[PDB]
Length: 227
Length: 227
Image 1 (cartoon, rainbow over the protein chains, first blue to last red):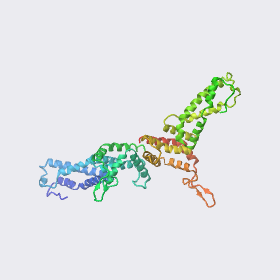
Image 2 (cartoon, rainbow over the protein chains, first blue to last red):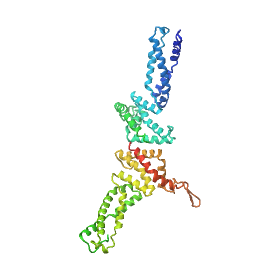
Image 3 (cartoon, one colour):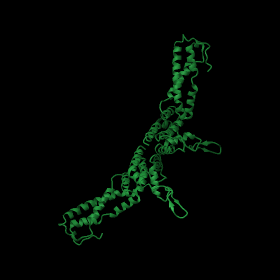
Image 4 (spheres, rainbow over the protein chains, first blue to last red):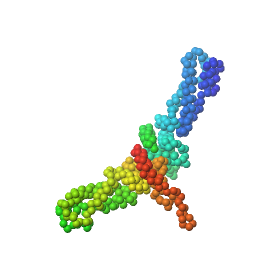
């Protein structure tokens, strides 16, 4: 924002005005949504960012030849505020984007949540994405209990899940409510000392999510393809 | 039972004692169960009956060559009680039998209920047979709400069943309760006269069952195979 050179050329001014107005806040917001599990908004912003980083790629290629031939652009000679590494590292956000329909984007987002060990969000997305996949097959509808198409899609998913992938739901639930909840059944005593009930190990979750969960999701998804 | 002539040879006494003790009551009971919709009990019998009619087939083939060469056998000359047509007509019950597991037997029984125009029994069997199919895939269980395997199998069938094939359930219900029921919504007046609330669609029942329903069942069964 305050990055203004005292004097510089017309080509220098055009490229610096381009860089000066790159929507870094959209990149930050994208990460905030992915982190806090606003999976729908995460995937929606995906196209805006493809354009933000494509504009940054070209601003950066220009800034690169500028610094490769630094002898010509001596106006940056004393400028501190402009950092290539800050912008080039921002281009890594490209690794979080995919092309396709919002269902295909959410599908990739699920993989991203497994890669980063974000277990809680990966499970909820694995649980609810098949419901959204089912709704597409039946022509579409809102994620509301008032919607008939959803009402039954959910019932099929929930029942097929409780039938074969009983564990998926058990984990998702445990992680959603956390240790201090009916899913963990800890015991509060007279002294205020709590003694945990259930004990699901770090490796039970790590292994299930990072190994079985993908395959289990894919097995659910082509099952509902027939529907 | 009262069939017992005064004169008889060793070959004719052999066959007449065989015919005299053919379990016709099992054939009658088989029909009683098929008629009243005790589909499970009827399917278990189909093996017993296969043997009853296989014994009757050879009894009859013997009785046939006996009557084809009637002049060698003039002992039956005055006997009234033995009549071929009664036994040969009983052999038609073979058309009601099939080979395989009880699930494959019930599957054929469904077709039989469509052939004879017994709509209600065909619908209930079409709606419940996919649950027993599902229960086989998950290792087996009792048709009780206490059984977990059933509880969800039913939920999948019912939901896939209320999502697509909406009509099947509507018909099955209507036919189960009949005209005097909440599914038909008739109106009883002050005087004592009832005025129906829906139209008895003789032809959509006939047409749905005898045309669409076998396809609607195969499509369901193909869907739950993946489960």
